Length: 232
Length: 232
Ligand SMILES: Nc1ncnc2c1ncn2[C@@H]1O[C@H](COP(=O)(O)OP(=O)(O)OP(=O)(O)O)[C@@H](O)[C@H]1O
Ligand SMILES: Nc1ncnc2c1ncn2[C@@H]1O[C@H](COP(=O)(O)OP(=O)(O)OP(=O)(O)O)[C@@H](O)[C@H]1O
Ligand SMILES: Cc1cn([C@H]2C[C@H](O)[C@@H](COP(=O)(O)OP(=O)(O)O)O2)c(=O)[nH]c1=O
Ligand SMILES: Cc1cn([C@H]2C[C@H](O)[C@@H](COP(=O)(O)OP(=O)(O)O)O2)c(=O)[nH]c1=O
Image (cartoon, rainbow over all chains, first blue to last red; front, side, top):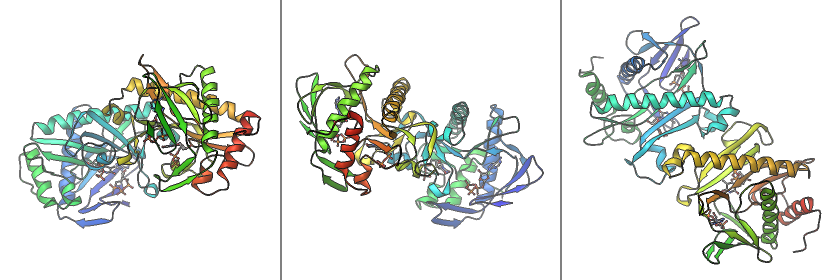
């Protein structure tokens, strides 16, 4: 059993674990905390929907099944210590790296690699740093190739629903065959979603910058995507 | 005429400029300042020596000639807005990016790209950011290829003189033929040099962290390399 900031990971046998989504939200290196009743359920459901879409499109993911409510059954992987960020529209930390305004449409997607390390506060890295960390160029290239394919699929699917995929974060691990498998979660916690018409945030930015009601925003995402009201 | 933090750039015609090295030193985003009589002369002389060595090895540089003392004649270029850092041994900012100690010998060199932008304080970037900045992948790859070749040459040459090239920064621009040309300076200001036996700094780190006498350290570098005492 491993209890993280937003999810719990419970071993089953040797091949699989339980990913349980909690109601907890954190931001700014965990210096901002709150709980949102039903956030876990929403993030679980939405992950399932995204993983199923991606699987239909030939993306290898850790998704195996659901275990009732906020719990997914997933394949255990040897995790890469990376957060892989894909960006279509300028927002968040990109504003400190490029002198471009919020909402600027990028000429092509940006991929950023962040080294998962709490003591160093998850610094950005490049391919050379990754190699020193034991991640080969070949591996990095496959990882970015998948992230960019995931981007296209989610972007297209979401645009047909009036949602702009601004940016998002993925994580990856290796399976026993040494294949690169998409892992962790895909939710309004780990993506920026803007309404196409109004350009307002329907994601964790609502909590990060106090823009209104997180649950309302997450429900709206769930409703726009499924065409149904969240039953919980 | 452009007066920078450590050097002055004076136009000649349309093809060339004067690079004048000043006695000024700055560090920590220019929050630490001092002047060292003779530093300009040392950095000029050492740049000349490095540019000549690199030219003999088939590296295209902006070096044209000397204009007496602290002044070099160099080719005017369309500058890339980059600082290109090559690292052999862990030091400086790399310690905040990888959990490795000062002096750790890297399994292979690291290349880091920093976007030259004072308002953003020169953030690290990757190939994708560079593209948005108008620098093609092809260009980035040629730039890194040159930096890594420069590394090998300087590393080998300096090791034969009992000096460890820990890391260093280069800058590049395009000439009228669209060729990538090595620019700016190569000095104890822009490199880490450690004595092979004692591992002590013979570079700007002496000023950054008050490790003794900058001029003495820079003289020692000049003496170890030329086999002669600095005449000024
Ligand atoms: N298929 C998988 N196999 C093994 N581990 C996984 C898998 N998917 C996700 N994980 C890891 O399980 C954890 C999920 O919990 P959570 O999101 O709360 O992480 P955290 O503890 O907050 O932060 P971190 O784990 O990044 O330090 C993360 O460490 C994630 O990388
Ligand atoms: N061959 C060249 N052609 C045109 N410009 C050059 C050439 N070589 C160096 N430069 C530029 O000239 C300037 C040298 O002066 P200096 O080192 O004092 O820069 P700075 O003003 O302190 O900092 P920066 O210029 O990076 O903001 C730098 O801007 C450098 O990029
Ligand atoms: C680096 C990182 C990004 N992300 C997601 C949130 C955003 O949708 C996108 C880019 O985030 P970014 O703008 O880099 O950081 P911040 O969340 O501090 O503004 O990736 C995470 O969920 N976790 C992370 O650790
Ligand atoms: C980024 C940068 C590096 N360098 C040189 C100094 C070091 O020899 C090497 C790596 O520096 P780095 O460790 O990144 O930064 P700091 O100088 O703040 O410790 O590159 C510069 O001269 N100017 C620069 O703007």
